[PDB]
Image (cartoon, rainbow, N blue to C red; front, side):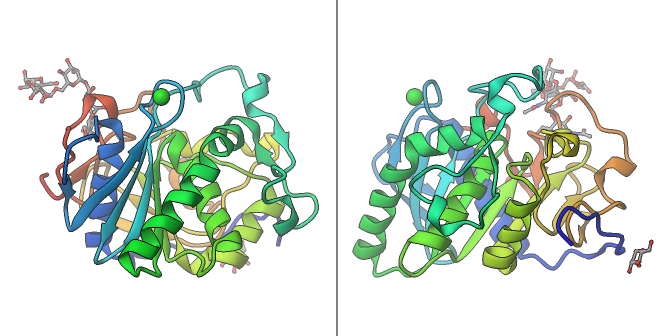
Length: 279
Ligand SMILES: *[C@@H]1O[C@H](CO)[C@@H](O[C@@H]2O[C@H](CO)[C@@H](O[C@@H]3O[C@H](CO[C@H]4O[C@H](CO)[C@@H](O)[C@H](O[C@H]5O[C@H](CO)[C@@H](O)[C@H](O)[C@@H]5O)[C@@H]4O)[C@@H](O)[C@H](O)[C@@H]3O)[C@H](O)[C@H]2NC(C)=O)[C@H](O)[C@H]1NC(C)=O
Ligand SMILES: *[C@H]1O[C@H](CO)[C@@H](O)[C@H](O)[C@@H]1O
Ligand SMILES: [Cl-]
């Protein structure tokens, strides 16, 4: 029920690893200058970019034959996730006015991630509607890594709830917790079969903010283990007890900025342009 912890055993990874590998390149490219004429990443053409990862996360919008209009959100450290949890960035708050009317009463979201999404949301919705129309494209995929993965989860819900035609898929890498148990179960209800959370190895970022602050993940993730390998399993349900805490975390960004199905998401340190499938 709300706030529970699944005990089910893991199963083989059922997700499309080609799609994951592509999505990892589409988001890695958001850590890079994306102003080039006609840039191509994997099967995708870049249509639009905004922001530079200093004041706001860079957002890149692509068209892809496999993912549709793909919106990728950078996750550079505009604030630190390893900081004092009493600070205001980690407080829970109501949904922003733009979408509160779509959510169950009692939904809460983390301030730092919600505010950063709210800075971008109307420009994202305008650009996605623009490019869906230009490309006769019904499918919208939202992709994010690190802080951009929690922003990406909020954006993927916003598209499903408020944009005509809803969401196709979301691919989220190294996803922090974002909302409370009401939120997590609503994600399952609205986008559960479109949701893909990928965690690599010993990454600590999916453990923060902690459950003791009222935060809960949606159901399911695929854990690549060992980190950077091609071996992965799906851990079903919310907060599966058999998953990542069974292997001690690392407290650096090595696996967080690791290899996801042959594509490195090295972040600012990484590959520019991104290289789908290169590892
Ligand atoms: C999963 O993959 C990620 C990368 O996507 C790994 O993250 C990196 O982790 C390392 C620590 O293990 C961090 O430390 C820095 O690494 C820098 C990169 O060093 C490699 O590449 C160099 C350039 O090609 C190369 O010269 C270097 O080789 C030298 O050092 C080796 C030991 O480190 C030694 O074995 C070699 O023979 C040679 O002397 C490395 O191959 C390095 O420049 C820094 O000095 C520092 O050590 C990186 O910052 C992390 N990268 C990112 C993007 O965060 C992660 O560790 C992988 N996970 C696992 C479990 O291995
Ligand atoms: C995990 O284990 C619990 C009991 O600990 C079961 O109720 C559940 O179905 C799953 O097997
Ligand atoms: Cl910026």
